[PDB]
Image (tube, rainbow, N blue to C red; front, side, top):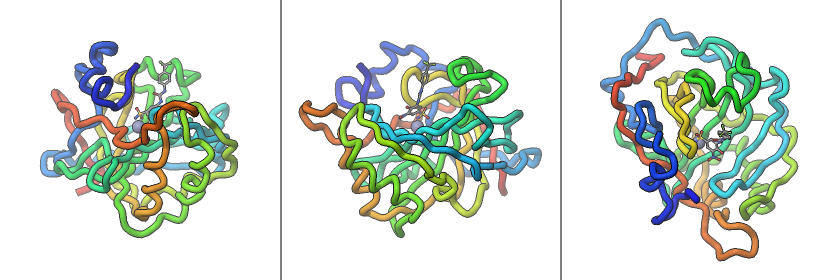
Length: 257
Ligand SMILES: NS(=O)(=O)c1cc(NC(=O)Nc2ccc(C(F)(F)F)cc2)c(O)c([N+](=O)[O-])c1
Ligand SMILES: [Zn+2]
């Protein structure tokens, strides 16, 4: 099946998922001079004080931290959104070197990694229903640059040894996702898609202007993970990012001037 290798990577995905060539695919390059300031955009409202993380999983493409979404515990609202979206998981995309790794780019600049906080629209009742709707998901995207260590990330870094290979999971309770946010919540927004198969075009993307810093050692630990399962030949989990797609008939809006 699909992956990020030479014979199954993003240039091949359209054969099994023809929407790979659709009208609102992600990620995109954010051209900061042609993005449009929109004064009618509201501030983001991030309410993560009651978040309940459950576990961390190596799913063979990235690693996911999953949360309890049976109730409105950790929600996102405001910004360009109408309604309440519940946090279900977060994951990252990263590179084999510091110069690449993010999925979105800013004026063609790539960052070392990108954090994706996935939320789904509660009016649709469950995540499976929400992904079938043009306004079903809202994903908060955060860039990582290499520099100073990010203290709030270290707990994630320390458990990666226990989920080295595909299909492994570990108990991961009491993790506070507020530790991953930058200082400012200024953002760009556009309508887009999932960036992995099935590539459904169900996402309101909210991409924060301000990156967070992580240390060289922290991102090094990311690139020790394994695409393969235990007992298979080792393939390091690196460069699990999809390249920028054509913007086509879309406009990037900015919350800031
Ligand atoms: N980069 S991203 O788009 O934000 C992104 C999304 C997911 N998760 C899913 O896509 N789940 C899912 C989607 C549809 C169905 C359905 F509807 F088919 F059942 C079932 C499950 C993910 O695991 C990663 N990742 O890399 O770990 C990245
Ligand atoms: Zn993602």
